[PDB]
Length: 116
Ligand SMILES: [Zn+2]
Image 1 (cartoon, rainbow, N blue to C red):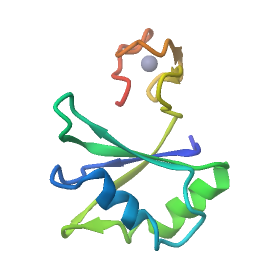
Image 2: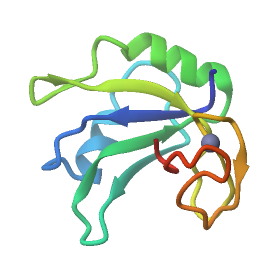
Image 3: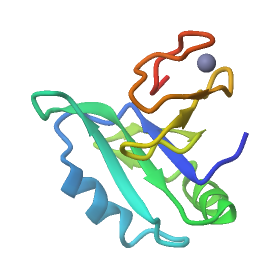
Image 4: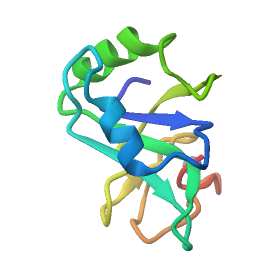
């Protein structure tokens, strides 16, 4: 599927949330609605981030304009579409498309992780 939210996987753990957002600027395409680096309970990066866009085509054009040019520290970064993952709100599973309660960490149907 295609969506407004974009999942960047395999990011170097040494990379901070400010390093990403500054790099998000000066990129081609519509500037995103938000840039979300997922961190640990200690605060260290979990290695993946969420880049949300306002409309659908702003995400596809950004996916189209950067699915070859997103290299950081020499390592290519995987780029996948993802259902919206906003703070506090409900989330649709990416593996079985079921809508889950917001406080649910694992999926109700297939048990897939919220960020899997
Ligand atoms: Zn599921």
